[PDB]
Amino acid sequence: ADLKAFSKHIYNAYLKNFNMTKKKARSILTGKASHTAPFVIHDIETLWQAEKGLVWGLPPYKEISVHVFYRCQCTTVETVRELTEFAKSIPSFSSLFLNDQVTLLKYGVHEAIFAMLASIVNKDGLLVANGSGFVTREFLRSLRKPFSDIIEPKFEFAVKFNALELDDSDLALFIAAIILCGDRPGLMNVPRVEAIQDTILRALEFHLQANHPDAQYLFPKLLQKMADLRQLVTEHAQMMQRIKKTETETSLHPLLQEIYKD
Ligand SMILES: O=C(O)CCCCCOc1ccccc1CN(C(=O)c1ccc(-c2cccnc2)cc1)C1CC1
Ligand SMILES: CCCCCCCO[C@@H]1O[C@H](CO)[C@@H](O)[C@H](O)[C@H]1O
């Protein structure tokens, strides 16, 4: 009965802390938010114009693939910051000891990052710089290995995910469900976390039958997506290890070194 209130507070935490909603993202991608459109980045020259000021600091320069890799890090570290504030706005999360909070964010943020990335992605590319840019998938494909191999799987997941047609209120509960996961290694108060997760799942199962009355099997499809996200992030972490090993001139932000340390 109270699930509607617990879930409303999660929605508010979502709207207060995340830079862009799926709502705002889809209106830009479809040309319904402004009479100015995102600047399309599809090669070195458009990339250079975007950096020069059209659209928008980092470690010293090295090459274009690496440059784009540093822009991906900057966006992930920033999204880690929004996920930390989102999580702390969930009272039951803030009741956990600080070390359990860190353990859940450490192993959950990338799963949650890649779930939210679908919102800014279509089959042809994705938005950057708060919607001022659009970077083409074909450009990101043209990057040299291993940087194109770490990017392209996220588009595959994103286009299938977007076929579920979730709105921001669905996503807020789904993200909370990914972060409050009782399985993370070294978790201290596991029973307390599992109870929170279960509450969010029940809130989510209720929310879907109200918001998507005609979509059947959506809840078990979303549970499957959470299992798919765990595997996508396992493969992402393996690809990050190879970059650490073979791309020695490429630096990793220190906060990402901590997440990938284990
Ligand atoms: O392991 C880590 O934590 C760091 C390593 C991540 C490496 C893989 O990152 C991927 C993969 C697929 C899709 C999106 C991203 C990065 N993201 C971007 O929004 C993003 C930002 C800027 C550009 C960009 C800017 C300028 C010119 N060209 C491209 C493109 C994409 C989302 C945060 C995930
Ligand atoms: C900002 C929230 C995201 C934080 C994710 C980074 C977690 O790094 C971990 O921080 C712990 C210190 O508490 C260390 O003990 C671990 O060795 C380290 O892996």
Image (cartoon, rainbow, N blue to C red):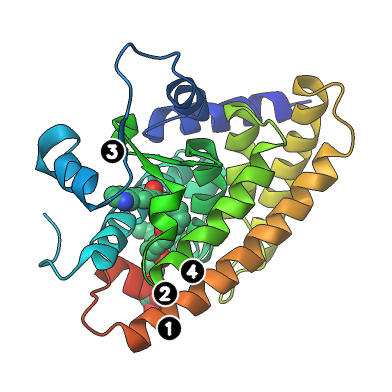
Please give the residue where the numbered disc 1 appears in the rendered image.
Answer: 242
Q: Is residue 171 in sight in this rendering?
A: yes
Pointers 2 and 4 in contact (CB under 8 A)? Answer: yes
In the image, taking residue 202 as reference, residue 229 lies left or right, namely: left
In the image, taking residue 3 as reference, residue 69 lies left or right, namely: left
Q: Which one is nearer the viewer's eye here, 154 or 199?
A: 154
Kind of residue at badge 3: Ala
- 236 up-or-down from 173: above or below: below
Please give the residue where the numbered disc 4 appears in the rendered image.
Answer: 149
Q: Between marks 3 and 1, how big is the CA–CA gap? A: 28 Å
Label 4 Cα neighbours within 10 Å, binned few <14 / some 14-19 / many ≥20: some
Q: Residue at x 43, y 82 (%)?
A: 241
Q: Residue at x 49, y 51 (%)?
A: 113
Q: Secondary structure at mark 2?
A: loop
In the image, taking residue 127 as reference, residue 254 lies left or right, namely: left
Please give the residue where the numbered disc 2 appears in the rendered image.
Answer: 146
Q: Residue at x 43, y 75 (%)?
A: 240
Q: Is residue 111 in sight in this rendering?
A: no
Q: Residue at x 82, y 38 (%)?
A: 218
Q: Which one is nearer the viewer's eye here, 44 or 77?
A: 44
Is label 3 within 8 A of ligand 1 (CB to nearest ligand atom)?
Answer: yes
Q: Position of residue 94 (x, y in %)?
A: 47, 48
Q: Between marks 1 and 2, how big is the CA–CA gap? A: 8 Å
Q: Between marks 2 and 4, how big is the CA–CA gap? A: 5 Å
Q: Between marks 3 and 2, how big is the CA–CA gap? A: 24 Å
State which quadrant residue 88 falls in.
top left
Ligand 1 placement by image quarter: bottom left
Please give the residue where the numbered disc 3 appears in the rendered image.
Answer: 129
